[PDB]
Image (cartoon, rainbow, N blue to C red; front, side, top):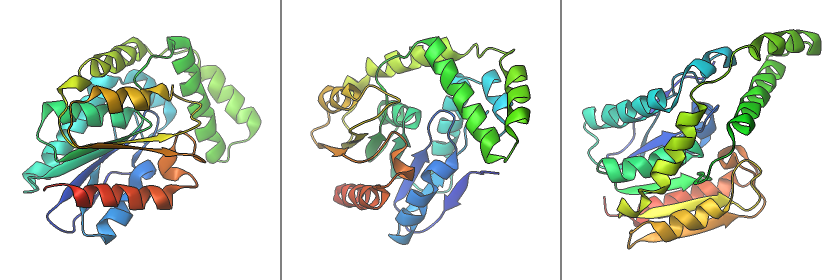
Length: 242
């Protein structure tokens, strides 16, 4: 069962944030890589995440943002003053929000959405996650159907709040001056890839870069170009003034 992680190495720290329906496993390989390069890493798990999908629908972005802020403070409290933030998908949106909320050395949003899917589409996405999760539990197709029958009886009321979160950060990214590396998969079937240009163009950061990953999908940390992504993130972090 996935759990948060903290790898303590050198004095430079990186906060790693996962995406909606994701968990710390989505950033664990990047954490081990950065630890091996001497960076301290911490990845939380948002409320309703890394547990049975049944628990997700009762949580929302107000809960998940508390987890993000508590994670930042966890690093600070351990004496790591200088923190970069790297985030996948929704974690990338939270990376941007931390970037104008609290002191950070740099931000790497990876496949972060700047625009809104419908509540129906977002809900379908939760349903897909729930079924994929039960498949990975090795449950028989019959058992999955019966469980999803039950699951569909409860709506997820916090989805309007997630739409509102995305629009709010979209409209505040002009407050960001921190060095920003925008990462985007070229073909991403989960988000509008125009988001990447919106972030790149919309921040006030004097120091910024963007890279497109040509053969990757949305969950880019788990996909086939992760080795390159790891090197690119490290090169970016090495270029910053800690």
